[PDB]
Image (tube, coloured by chain):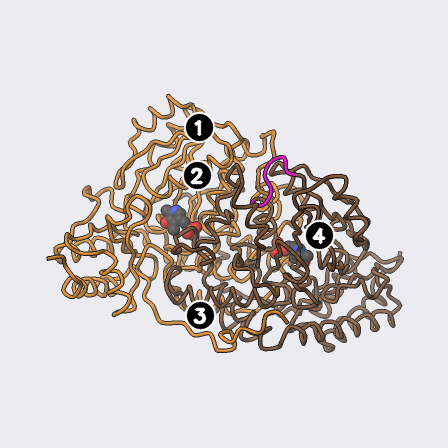
Chain colours: A orange, B brown
């Protein structure tokens, strides 16, 4: 045998106990861990289809939509974004992008790759879009689709959504919203707000393991995806196939790809947990936990990166890196000494911020206090330039 | 609020006990279940990178490769196939496909979608490709890439691989092989056999949960993917990003997408298990379990769909549907009365076969006895036209 058994693999798997207070992934509550330890069932079994049906109802609840074209993407949040774009956008389609952070930037990248005519509305980290800014782009660029990040987890910004769907429809444009970091943590009403494509991820406020994502499409979006004269560049993400297998159309469920059965157990449990809590209660929990964190951070002498409180994302808080410190020193101090994960910035916000997440079961006073004391220590014991 | 908490979600999760003896997914051994119940760690933590590095070594062992561009794809077997094609193939590229079952048909579909000029070598289910046939395709079509299914789990066929790599390389063609169903169950030597892109999946003989897949690229494949004139149509599957995050290039890892941490625990344990068993021992187990199954099926009067034993895929056996029965009756009887899943056909083998999987820890004479007993009962209780 060219390759002999790797000796590292003959040792038991061991993992450290880490408090994940970054922008994701989040820690798992006991019920979600327990679901992930269950035995397999047939991936096209009646029982699996029931679990899928229940997850669909759970997505319809947390998104606040009655869209029948609602399902799980078998991939991370990026995969759901790519699924939205590859199905909705044909080569040459005008695509307007709220490029105010890494997520808009990734939407630009995907749009470019799949041949769309991409028109970024570029903003610096911390920026957000007004209706007038969006209408100017809608008027100048005549897009079939607008992408807006709801929770800009790379900058800590909460993008208002009211009226954007209506405005987009007046220009015959579809509204696609990224709610990966916002879902569960802040108000979101898919149908009410006129959103045509809404997606989120498993590992943020829902506290499920990463690797699955949630997506829903309005009838307007469905029409565009089913009317195109080219096939999408992806088979794995082809919505006609996925809609069928997820029981959204008029035909028997056909084999497309094997869904991640065990991850669906855990995703289903994560949707049950928030259905038990109640959406509005969850919003309150995150709203109150973030207010408390904001106070404790400012009492340390730290400056919140988003200056307008109304624009602050409860689930991911950006903090200006204090003068004289290497943000990497602070972040490593906190994990190295306290087994607490926080993060620096990402894309445009790199070097400029620290990012602290309050996600689902982790959005608690106790965790605010732990991260507050960790930063207090890091500020006292990290090197500060002379 | 428009939508109230779903009543069904307020009930507790409850799963039936099923013995999964179809072509996959397979049942999970204790260590893999235990790993699935663990707590999260940072998706970009040093400890996560260690686990990933160990997984990479494990893939290099089960594939028998030293290729540094070896990693996990964050999606099912299909996703690994798509990752291979969207990175290797550029619009206009000639793509020669072994369409002898569903998996070649799927490769055709992906290739068409991404603008390749696709050349299927279409073969009836149960067929396999000779060196002569492929060279005729290489002669005619001058492809940049050949797709061949190793373990054709829709037809039960074990495709010979020796000599195909050397042949493709003479014709400056890359060899892409699907080993989702063969990995761990039958001999496979990526580097020895000159395979340029090799992929498998988590939920076949490895007995990990479905949702991840395994992929490796040779230096020749890397050269193609890294000298494209256009970016791949996929960002999620762009190999330059993926190679970097998986520590395969000479740059520090940068965030691409969040890897499925818990699934990686489980895959790690699945690779540890087969590392503990030994590849050749795994091949032995599957070979002997399949031989036992073939004899028991034949004793029932059932006919094996692949007649040459040398061409039978140990991990997924095709049985010709017995004359006079509705195969759906048999499949239903087996789950309803014996809590065993088997399958009918898929793609070209639809309606023509039953499919019985023998996968990893499930590949046992006990399970052969269980499915044989259940089939015996189905043949005498299912109505016969
Ligand atoms: C975390 C995140 C993503 C990316 O999700 P992945 O699971 O890493 O692919 C996308 N958008 C937002 C707002 C996010 O917070
Ligand atoms: C099961 C299988 C696949 C596809 O795997 P999925 O996880 O269902 O996407 C591809 N090739 C072969 C040979 C398979 O057996």
- Mark 4 element type: strand
Question: Dot 4 surroundings within 10 Å: few (below 14), some, or many (20 or more)?
Answer: many
Label the magenta part by its dominant secondary structure.
Answer: loop
C-beta proximity under 8 Å, tags 3 and 2: no
Q: Quadrant of the N terminus of chain B?
A: top left
Residue at the spot of label 2? A109
- Marks 3, 1: nearer the viewer: 3
Task: Please identify the quarter of the rendering in which residue A127 is found.
Answer: top left
Which numbered disc flags the more N-terminal residue, 2 or 1? 2
Give percent across and percent down for residue B83: 56, 49
Distance in Å between CA atoms under marks 3 and 1: 44 Å
Q: Nearer the viewer, mark 3 or mark 2?
A: 2
Residue beneath the point at 63% across and 61% down: B191
- Spatial distance from mark 4 to mark 2, Cα to Cα? 32 Å
Residue that label 3 marks: B38
Depth check, front residue: B270 or A43: B270
Q: Which residue is mark 4?
A: B148
SS for callout 2: helix
- Residue A173: image tag: 1
């Amino acid at each position: 045998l060219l390759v002999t058994p790797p000796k590292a693999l003959l040792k038991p798997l061991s993992i450290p106990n880490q408090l994940l207070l970054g922008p994701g992934p989040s820690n798992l509550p006991p019920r979600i861990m327990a679901a992930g330890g269950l035995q397999m069932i047939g991936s096209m079994s009646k029982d699996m289809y029931q679990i899928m049906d229940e997850i669909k109802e759970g997505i319809q609840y947390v998104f606040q939509t009655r869209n029948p074209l609602t399902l799980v993407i078998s991939g991370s949040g990026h995969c759901a974004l790519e699924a939205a774009l590859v199905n909705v956008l044909e080569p040459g389609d005008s695509f307007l992008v709220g490029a105010n952070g890494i997520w808009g930037q990734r939407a630009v990248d995907i749009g470019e790759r799949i041949g769309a005519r991409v028109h970024p509305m570029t903003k610096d980290p911390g920026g957000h879009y007004t209706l007038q800014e969006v209408e100017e782009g809608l008027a100048q660029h005549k897009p079939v689709l607008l992408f807006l990040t709801h929770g800009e987890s790379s900058t800590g910004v909460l993008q208002p959504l009211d009226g954007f769907g209506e405005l987009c429809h007046r220009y015959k444009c579809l509204l696609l919203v990224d709610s990966v970091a916002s879902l569960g943590g802040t108000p979101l009403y898919m149908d009410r707000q006129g959103i045509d494509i809404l997606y989120s991820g498993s590992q943020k406020a829902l506290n499920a393991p990463p690797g699955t994502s949630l997506i829903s499409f309005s009838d307007k979006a469905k029409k565009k995806m089913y009317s195109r004269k080219t096939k999408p560049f992806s088979f794995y993400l082809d919505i006609k196939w996925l809609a069928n297998f997820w029981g959204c159309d008029d035909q028997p469920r056909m084999y497309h790809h094997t869904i991640p059965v065990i991850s669906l157990y855990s995703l289903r449990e994560s949707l049950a947990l928030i259905a038990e809590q109640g959406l509005e209660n969850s919003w309150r929990q995150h709203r109150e936990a973030a207010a408390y964190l904001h106070g404790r951070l400012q009492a340390l002498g730290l400056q919140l990166f988003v200056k307008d409180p109304a624009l602050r994302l409860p689930t991911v808080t950006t903090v200006a890196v204090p003068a004289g410190y290497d943000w990497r020193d602070i972040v490593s101090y906190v994990i190295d000494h306290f087994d607490i994960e926080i993060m620096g910035g990402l894309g445009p916000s790199t070097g400029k911020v620290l990012r602290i997440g309050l996600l689902g079961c982790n959005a608690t006073r106790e965790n605010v206090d732990r991260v507050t004391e960790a930063l207090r220590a890091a500020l006292q014991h990290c090197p500060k330039k002379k």
